[PDB]
Image (cartoon, rainbow, N blue to C red; front, side, top):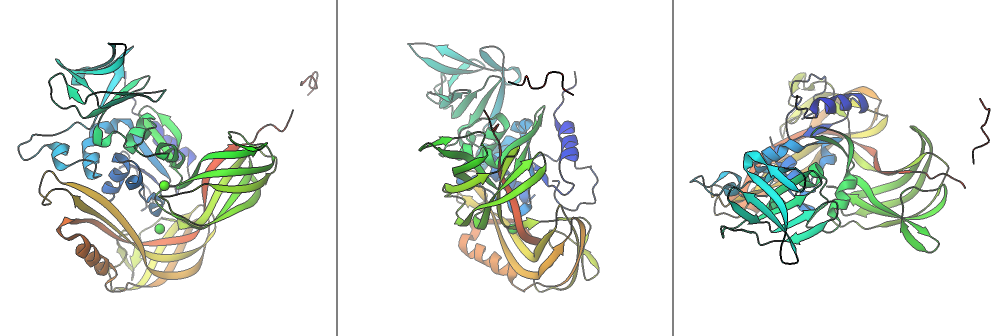
Length: 488
Ligand SMILES: [Ca+2]
Ligand SMILES: [Cl-]
């Protein structure tokens, strides 16, 4: 029997259900041979940022995917096999842990999977058997790896969230710094530094985080829209609502569906990687795919994406099949649909111009709807900052990735974009020192601890953009159906 990975089905899905201007990304380069007119994103500086997302948890894992115009993020269960690399590249583990020190010793297995085989979990190839033992009025998890038995730091069974401590030691006496997650069909064995990583959450639906509320927020930013085999396609919503409360007969109640009529709602907002600024809230009433009313319900001048707070609104919802909550604010749209030229010449679309340069810049960009855009030149620095070790060459070093973006210069106000391809022509001036200036700043701040991994200079179209925060089904509005005998 063939092993279906899920990839063939997932790409087919993406091709049939998403805009031709949508951006998908992934760890693995499946699909590299697919031909497009698109010079945009369908998936090595960005590797550190992908890994930063996947290998980490909480605040530091909040990467600004919006600046990439990211639409879909593909999670592949088989990436456990690449997880040391991802952990290393994302700053979760040291070089030593990643693949051994200079004597090939000390390497760590970040993620191992076991298959449920009734009451017990196995991986033949790794010679692993995980089982629950009952001894001394109590439960414990035993991980057997060859002849030695091992006690995980912590184990958590799902469904349940049933926590159960252990020693973090083997019968050997030797350390066992692993966490176990038991699900109905998988047993995940994770090294402690990556036990609550986002990959573990999204690959295996484990709702754990070292941080309070973080798993719940994450799941509103990444919506499973399709799955097959070992592939889950998540839609990215940078601004999302993870919990709504209706104020009902004097107390707040968590709600699923909403009835038409007046409501007072408390919206719990998760902002992922970027702040809310000068934002308007809406509700769009929808019948199927038709939008029948747009209602402004609020504004948010500013919310910090690391310290978000609930928002109270009052709304009269008309009758409709479902309600879509929208956040509108400034952000990027447009995918490059042909090559980019400076002064007649084809240039790199990731490095449009060097500091000091000048000239006619020619872009062709595709958008899904009409907008009025401003065009900027935007810089992106992806770099590493050594944490630990006494040198970039020391094996006890880990490297923490960073991504800073800033707008270098505005090139044009009030471009009218049209659904489909748009040809754009403008005069462009790179200030000398735009890049070097920032490079020096980082150098001065971090010293030898700094490794720059990528610098980009990119054209970016800024518009009032609509973001989908959540979709809520309407409830039936009342309240025998013999009315239809001998009808039609
Ligand atoms: Ca956040
Ligand atoms: Cl941006």
